[PDB]
Each structure stands twice: as structure tokens, then as C-alpha cells.
Image 1: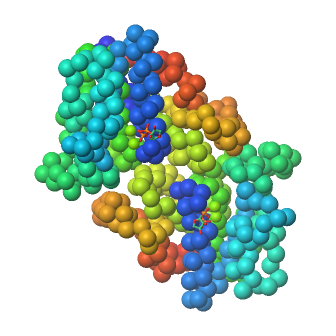
Image 2 (image 1 turned 180 degrees about the vertical axis):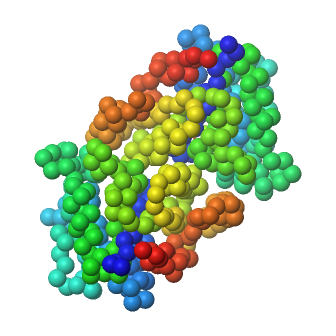
Image 3 (image 1 turned 180 degrees about the horizontal axis):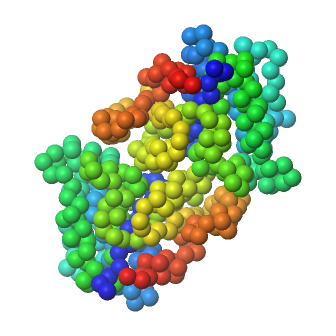
Length: 224
Length: 224
Ligand SMILES: [Mg+2]
Ligand SMILES: [Mg+2]
Ligand SMILES: [Mg+2]
Ligand SMILES: [Mg+2]
């Protein structure tokens, strides 16, 4: 087949999508699985002044595989506003609704040249892109598998389960992975006991990202 | 009929359930709608040393209607652990799984003496109480209407919509209300534009709690 595609969403902005995506792509590349990082939509940016956005960090990693890549090759809709993409678009670019059909074509083109195409969303699954589509809808259009990154703070149980409920209600392969900090041992006392119980009782377990690079690469590449 | 019952859940712990519940009960009581505040399950407490838990604050308000109330009349399962109730129960009281049938009876008894019985949950909708039941399941057993309090920070759109999706998928009347801080005008710039759009497109709109005391009292009391 052409390259596999993995969408990365999260419980929350700042949960760890970009960090975990970069660590996963680094691992995949080190294993000989040629992997590109894309950020098709990004808010809260000012490219004239700042070169540390998600798409910039992705570009730096990606140029280890293709020196010719530029920011516009890997990120397509970029806004100054810190808001959902739909709202930034309506305010900053009212004449140009985000075209997810076009994005689906651009992203799928990278499956020609890469074994794995990692696509970071913005915000969370329900975050609106257009009047009709949210980030989950975009992932469904892409026919990507899904990796949902969770925070490791109090309340992760609820956040993970709300996303589990939404994901299991739609027709896509997914995994939920906790982005665990190593100074955080409260996790192991407070939340982990329930993650363990849940995993005995669920066919799709919640994993810890940092323990799961091999299984997540396997997940991303499996099947058609 | 006997008194109505309103369950109060949230996007997150610390979202505002207790503050908003107390403000709603105060408003209801001031309007002649006799209203009790209950906290059947509470974690993170130490009643030997601290008298500022949710059940304590509820008790103070409630004693304006019944001097005879004590903490044990309004809160039934209390744990030291900061965790989901299921986990606190397994650790601190392994022989006594939380009995939601018993809680349903105790809570419904207050519908004899009150026009409105407000029941604050713990944690979020998906937070586990027993191996089989979460907070939403408990609310469904209670046949309560639901008020879900949202935080007013970045990411509220996603959190509200994840809860909307879960709630609209089950057979209960609900409202989602944002607990807005008055020093927060970023809300109006960043999130409100989407709340407005959503509300044009949804039969069940997301409201701002502070604007909505009358409509929420109406909601709580309507119908059977
Ligand atoms: Mg971010
Ligand atoms: Mg990011
Ligand atoms: Mg609290
Ligand atoms: Mg509370």
C-alpha cells in the first residue's frame, strides 16, 4: 500500500501532541520507517516574528529527510488568533473557509514518499474547522488511524473516557496514550489504579505514551 | 409531583460546581422555591481537621432551612484520597462498594420536603463510582435533570462539546452552563464567538451560568 497516516489529537491544547509526535517520528525514523510530521492547521502563530511554532519544529525534524521542505509544504492554514480554527478563519480570512477536501489530497500525497505520515490536529477532537467539520471529522475524511494524547494531571480519567466514548462511537482505529512526566509520581498513586482496572475491562486499553513507542509504531503501520 | 432533582456535574473538578450550585440554590430559595444542596460522595476530605468541604459549605446554607441537618444527612460516602470515588473506596473502604440504589432512595426522600433537590457529583460525567457505574449512570438512575458546569478557559469549546456528545447520546434533559469570571474578557473574544454560532445551530444551547439563573431554575422545575 502507500504510506500509512496517523492523526494526533489530544484531550487539551498543551497536552503533548507536538512533543509526542516528534518523539514517535524520531523512533520510527530510527527504526527505518520513513516518517514525516505535518501540521496542516495552526492557530496562535506569527511567522514574521517567531519560528518556534509546531510547524517550525516539524520542519526542522523533517529536513533531516528532505532539505527542500519549507513551512508552506507542511502547514497550510495559519492564523494569528488563539482560538478554534473556524473562528480564526472567520475573523482573519473570511473569504477562505478551510478546505478539508484539498487538505485530504495534500496529506495523502505524502503517502507516496513516506512510510508514515503523522498529522497533528489543533485543539481537541471537537474543535471546529468549518461550520460543518471538526477535527474528528477531518480525521475520518483522511481515513487515518487516531492517536489521542492525554495529559497526566488530575482529571485525566474523565478526559480520557469522554474521548473514548466519542471515538468508539465512530468508525476509526484509535489509541489513547497518556503523556506522563517523570517528576509526576502522583499519577501512579491517583490515576493509574483506574487505568489498570479499565484496561482489564476494555478491549482498547489506555496506554502510557513513554512506555508505548514500539506498540504505537506497530499500531500506526498495521493492516491496510 | 414531589420535588424536582437537578444533578450538577462539570467539565472538570474545580470548574465551579459547588459555587454555582450554591448561587442557584440561593436564587431558588429567594424566589420561594425551597431548595436543598446535597453532596452524596466526596473525595479529598478530612472532616476531623477541616470543615470547608463541599458538604460543609452546603450544610451551612442548608441550615437556613433546617437547623437539625448534620453533615451525615447530606453526604454519605466520604474519603481522604484525592482520586475518583471508585479508587478511594477500593483503597479506604474495600468492603463497602458505593451503593447507588441506597443513595437513590436517600436523595429521593428529600423530594418530600423540598421543591428542588440539588445533587452535586464529584469529578466529571465519566468519573467511576463503582465497577459498573459512573457519575452519569448515577444521574440516570436518579432520573434527575442535568446541569453541567464548564470552565471559562481556553479549551472550553472542546470540553463542552465532548460532554454534549455524551449527554445527547443518553436519555436525560440537560443544560451546559459556562462559569464565567468577570476578570475574564478573553472569553468574549476567543470562545464566545463559537458559542454563539453553536447556539444558532443547536436545539440545546450552551449558556453562561451568570446570565442564566432564571432559566436554570425554570429548567430544573419544568414538567414532571
Ligand atoms: Mg500547543
Ligand atoms: Mg502542538
Ligand atoms: Mg472541587
Ligand atoms: Mg465541588
